[PDB]
Structure formats: C-alpha cells, structure tokens
Amino acid sequence: TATREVDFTVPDVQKILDDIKALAAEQVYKIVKVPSISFRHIVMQSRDRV
Amino acid sequence: HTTDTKVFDKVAASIFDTVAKCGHEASPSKTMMTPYSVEKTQTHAKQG
Amino acid sequence: YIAPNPRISSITLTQRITTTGPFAILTGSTPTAQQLNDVRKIYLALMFPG
Amino acid sequence: NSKDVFYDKFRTEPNRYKALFRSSFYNESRRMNEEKILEAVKYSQKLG
Image 1 (cartoon, rainbow over the protein chains, first blue to last red):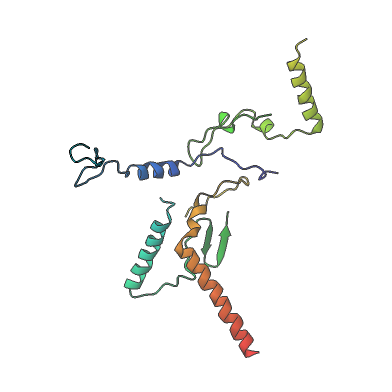
Image 2 (cartoon, rainbow over the protein chains, first blue to last red):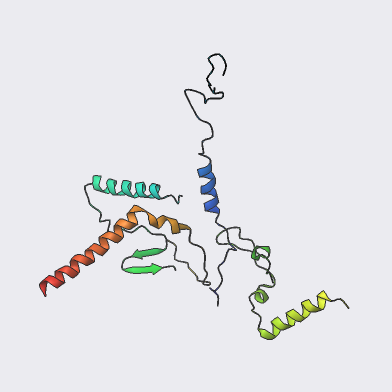
C-alpha cells in the first residue's frame, strides 16, 4: 500500500545546482573572420542594371 | 555532477589509465561503479 | 476529484529534517466505499443550495 | 561511515541516473560477462 503511488514531495537541489553550473558555460557570441552577407544581386539579360 | 554519457566514459577511462600507469591492472569486468548498490567484505546491500 | 499539493503541509529544509503537520495521522488514511459515497453526498448537497 | 542508522518507510522515487546506462562502460561490462558465459558453456560442451 505504501509504495503504490510515485512521490514528488521532495525536490533534488543538487540537480538544480548542477544544471545552473552547466548553464553558466553556455556561449552566446561567435568569433568570425568575415561578416555574413547582407545584400545580394540578381542579374538579368541587361549589362547596366541589377 | 553530470548525466552526460561521454563525460562519464572519459572519466572511467582516465581512472583505468591511472591504475595501469601505477604498475597494476584493474579488471573492468568486475570493477564496480554504481549508484544504488554497495558491496563490502562479502556484504551486499541493494536499495537499503 | 483532485487532491491538494503534498508540499502545502510539509517543507523539507534538508534531506534529513522535515516539518510535521498537525493532522499527519488523518492524511495517511484511505477512504472506504461508504465514506466515498458520503463525500459524493456532501458535494451533491453543496451544488444544490436549498 | 557512521553507524547510528534507523529505518523509517518504503518509498518510490524517479531514477535520475536512468540515462547514464547507455554508456560504453556498461555495454562493455555486459559484453564481457556474456562472452565469459559463452566460453564456459562451450568448454562444458566440448568436454562432455
């Protein structure tokens, strides 16, 4: 009778602390040599306008 | 302090390599690394 | 029917120390058939006032 | 290592380490144990 229902009345603080410690090492920015392309060009049968 | 797989694997590998470097050999077949079971001096305990 | 959250009556400061509710003996009880029927009667009386 | 132990109740709780057992170390331990059983049984079958 005692072990019929799964229990959640006690939390796991060590798991929370480990998760926060792991999250502290997340990287947001990047280091690049060349910035990404912002404008591109479509060409047609013309030789003066795009 | 982890639940990731490869970190645990590399930790176990480091332990075994250290034992080998100490001029000994530890059998991985019977080496124990477990959460919920304890054995000591021919005494066995499982889940309390 | 929904039971209340078990954390309301007790909080665990540590893995070893927990607070104790005054009615802990009653909370461990489990209703029989007759008592459950009486609970249904009580709610039926609540839903129809007079 | 303290010996002042008392026992209260049986409980059930979720297993935090359930995902760790898919690691290489446990697979290798299981493999070595089962293959050891295989050499035992084949030696017994060869002798008699």
